[PDB]
Length: 144
Image (cartoon, rainbow, N blue to C red; front, side, top):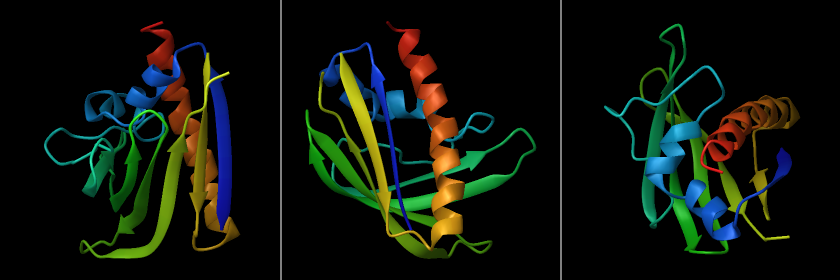
């Protein structure tokens, strides 16, 4: 019910943080490879506190909506937000907390997702995040 992922990048921590907090940048790699978020419906931005949400659509038209609350935004340091998927009738279930933290070295990113349904879910999310980070990595290497 608790997962941890991390990767280093040849960019400046200031940059890495902007890439994991700014909506313009977030909307670039959000969601696993294969699915995207329609500009039509979302509020993906961890730059300020308050409600955040975002639906994802895959290559087959399947929609997935996840909501949350940005709990803390430490501009250079880190961000933290609430996590909850939505029902077939727009009803969010089990809630979790996601945290993106930087820390230079270049700069490395730590993704920590806790309080998930169980282990079988702590896996499904890990691979999901893993898949989604590939898109960030690529997005970064394109901006150098």
